[PDB]
Image (cartoon, grey):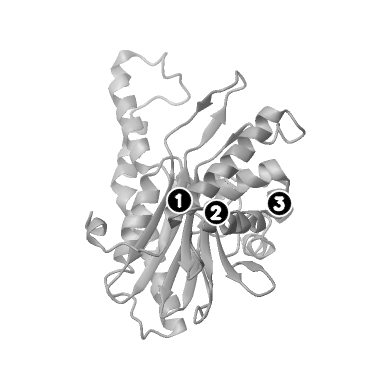
Amino acid sequence: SWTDDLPLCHLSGVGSASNRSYSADGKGTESHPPEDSWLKFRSENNCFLYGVFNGYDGNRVTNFVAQRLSAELLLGQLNAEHAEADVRRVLLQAFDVVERSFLESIDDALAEKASLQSQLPEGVPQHQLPPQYQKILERLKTLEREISGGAMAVVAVLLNNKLYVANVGTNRALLCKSTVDGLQVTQLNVDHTTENEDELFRLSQLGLDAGKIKQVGIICGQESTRRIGDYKVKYGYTDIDLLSAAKSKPIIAEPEIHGAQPLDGVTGFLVLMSEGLYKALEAAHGPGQANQEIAAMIDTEFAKQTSLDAVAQAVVDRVKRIHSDTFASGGERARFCPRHEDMTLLVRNFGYPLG
């Protein structure tokens, strides 16, 4: 709540939308609690900090990642004067701390879990388990809710018209410069997926069957090879099939910082988006060529709207309608768009004309 006190960024806007599971019934959409989250703060130093997070297994970690990353970057940890390698250190530490402190938070609760499972008979139905054991089972679920969760992240720091982008998964971060030729969409981050050869290298260097991983694509329902939290994959990776034989942690929370961009005399806008957004547009429009469309869509709405929040929200709502139309149209991509995931879109304006 100390984050509430921080001054907010007049030059940034956000648009978001909850997961929807289109019912075949027709005209009906079920939704679980949203797990994405974001972050748009200006410090005293004119050090701007943006972030879009992508939770799963609940939004506990999302909120922790945000609240803590704020404390590790917006209390003077970043200064104007810092050199490029100077800042790239402060980020690496901030993210390290976050991952260390998260796992430390749940240690007490994880130990309690171990104890209460020791009290419970192995390989047994819950409804068939006598009333005696019901109190334990509730507490194990209470605990589970508390410790469970993970989060992909993508964070951008603006410091003296230098843009640094720390990324920990599938969340994307396009820089959109409007040159004379057109709008130059250029993705600053890199998708840490099971198809990133560079990540397949790091996974191979842990003695993993990179071909099998590459084949399946998903790892416990996620395709992200880097995540913050999720004790399941940070601790019990030995119990996962694909990760059975890893020298050290297969899923890691080390950010891939990306070099400074000179935003001196640049006109354009920055796009931090979640996985859910672009993943949904591809699901309806066909693979690849997605970053492009959204960057444009924002470009369109940039003149059509009166606020960056509306500009972002405009676009998210189109992607939603595209996906929904594509389901109800009954076309060839209707099987591709039965549902979608929490969408988030943050837009930092670099002078680009609004309204």
Q: Quadrant of residue 239?
A: top right
Which residue is the site of mark 3? 214
Which residue is the site of mark 2? 301
On residue 310, the disc is: 1
Say if mark 2 contacts mark 1, CB within 8 Å.
yes
Q: Is residue 255 or residue 131 the one in the foreground?
A: 255
The disc, 3 or 2, on the residue closer to the chain's N-terminal end is 3
Say if mark 3 contacts mark 1, CB within 8 Å.
no
Instruction: Mark yes or no: residue 55 visible.
Output: no
The amino acid at mark 1 is Ala
The amino acid at mark 2 is Glu
Q: Is residue 220 or residue 289 the one in the foreground?
A: 289
Count residues near mark 3 (Cα–Cα under 10 Å), then give few for <14, some for 14-19, many for 20+.
some
Q: Residue at x 30, y 51 (%)?
A: 105
User: Where residue 237 sits: x, y (%)?
Assistant: 53, 48
The amino acid at mark 3 is Lys
User: Where residue 90 sits: x, y (%)?
Assistant: 38, 74
